[PDB]
Image: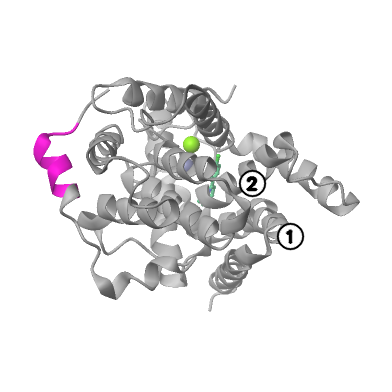
């Protein structure tokens, strides 16, 4: 577990978000992309507005942030950018559903989002091992000196957020998303979905985690495009690691077959992304704008495929 300098955590402490972004950042389609030096700042901002300025000692919280930063790796996609992008989408979901989520949930979900791919190497998991590792990394960072941002909580408050965070992180394993979303489909339609049921809560939170994880598909077209190149630059670098031992990479992880990508995107939107946001919109109607953006980008990929 690496840790931040004093100057890193102190630098975050003096950050103020510039005002011109104050409305942007509440938008589901907000792109953090242009603002690299602000990304830790942005996360402080979001925590402050979702959970309140007096929810974590500023000090330990900046300590936590800058250190989580240093346990991400400088790979194309599963890096610090993605963790802040994921966090932000969760912030937007929290903001438009405020009355449904407990304080304990709101703090745990933002932190878990930030930590969701901790120490990702960029190579494919190809049971939920990666996610269980991510959660363990999160425990390590928490255990560190001056780093336990939950110190001001009770024994059962603590032993409960840790659990909200474990479940959240695990839920980011797309293999589990399918059965969970199916499960949620059934419940909702039978009318048997109970938010007062803790196990049902966990299911919905699962879907939220997926919806955040994948939120690159819900940005503006110019942004959605550039971000596809980032994910793909990792499949390909892994496929190269296949080639280097004469192995054939599956055709997604071969950068020779580069013009496969828009069809791959369309497939993925149809099989994975649209259902995800579809169901989420149904359980949480204020997240509609994610579904709309996803559809808009689906429609763009068709045009590339049809050569327009
Ligand atoms: C955000 C984004 C765009 C995209 N395109 C193709 C494939 C995937 C993908 C993502 C996660 C997993 Cl586990 C598997 C595949 N993704 N993810
Ligand atoms: Mg992950
Ligand atoms: Zn992720």
User: What secondary structure is found at the residue carrying circle 2?
Assistant: helix
Reply yes or no: does residue 42 show up in magenta.
Answer: no
- Toward the bottom, the furthest residue is 308
The stretch of residues the image draws in magenta is 4-12
Residue 240 seen in the figure: yes
Look at the image and tell me whether residue 253 can be seen. no
Taking the spot 67% from the left edge, 59% from the top edge, the residue there is 284
Q: Which residue is mark 2?
A: 207
Residue 16: image location, x then y, percent: 21, 61
Q: Is residue 202 above or below residue 84?
A: above
| Residue at horizontal 69 percent and vertical 52 percent from the top | 271
> Residue under circle 1?
282
Question: Residue 28, how many percent across, how many down?
Answer: 49, 65
Q: Is residue 44 above or below residue 21?
A: above
The residue lying toward the viewer, choosing from 87 and 224, is 87
Disc 2 crowd rating (10 Å Cα; few below 14, some 14-19, many 20+) is many
Q: Magenta part mainly helix, strand or loop?
A: helix
Separation (CA) of disc 1 from disc 2? 11 Å
Determine the image quadrant of residue 199: top right
Q: Is mark 2 within 8 Å of ligand 3?
A: no
Classify residue 206 as left or right of residue 250.
right
Quarter placement of the N terminus? top left
List x then y, in percent, for residue 235: 44, 41
Q: Nearer the viewer, residue 300 or 251?
A: 300
User: Left or right: where does residue 220 sit relative to residue 173?
Assistant: left
Farthest residue, direction right: 190
How many numbered circles are shown?
2
Secondary structure of residue under mark 1 = helix
């Amino acid at each position: 577990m690496s840790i931040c300098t004093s100057e890193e955590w102190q630098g975050l402490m003096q950050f103020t978000l510039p005002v011109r972004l104050c409305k942007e950042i509440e938008l589901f389609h907000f792109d953090i992309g242009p603002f690299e030096n602000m990304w830790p700042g942005i996360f402080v901002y979001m925590v402050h507005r979702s959970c309140g300025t007096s929810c974590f000692e500023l000090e330990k919280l900046c300590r936590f942030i800058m250190s989580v930063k240093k346990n991400y790796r400088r790979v194309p996609y599963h890096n610090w950018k993605h963790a802040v992008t994921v966090a932000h989408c969760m912030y937007a979901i929290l903001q438009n559903n405020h009355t449904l989520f407990t304080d304990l949930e709101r703090k745990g979900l933002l932190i878990a989002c930030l930590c969701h791919d901790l120490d990702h190497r960029g190579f494919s998991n190809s049971t939920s091992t990666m996610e269980q590792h991510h959660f363990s990394q999160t425990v390590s960072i928490l255990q560190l000196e001056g780093h336990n941002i939950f110190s001001t909580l009770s024994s059962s408050e603590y032993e409960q957020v840790l659990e909200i965070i474990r479940k959240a992180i695990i839920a980011t394993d797309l293999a589990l998303y399918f059965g969970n979303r199916k499960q949620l489909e059934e419940m909702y339609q039978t009318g048997s979905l109970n938010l007062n049921n803790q196990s049902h809560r966990d299911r919905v939170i699962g879907l939220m985690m997926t919806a955040c994880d994948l939120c690159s598909v819900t940005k503006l077209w110019p942004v959605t495009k550039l971000t596809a190149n980032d994910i793909y630059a990792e499949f390909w670098a892994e496929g190269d690691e296949m080639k280097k031992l004469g192995i054939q990479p599956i055709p997604m992880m071969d950068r020779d077959k580069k013009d496969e990508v828009p069809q791959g995107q369309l497939g993925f939107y149809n099989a994975v992304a649209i259902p995800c946001y579809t169901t989420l919109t149904q359980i949480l109607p204020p997240t509609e704008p994610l579904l709309k953006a996803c559809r808009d980008n689906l429609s763009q990929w068709e045009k590339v495929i049809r050569g327009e």
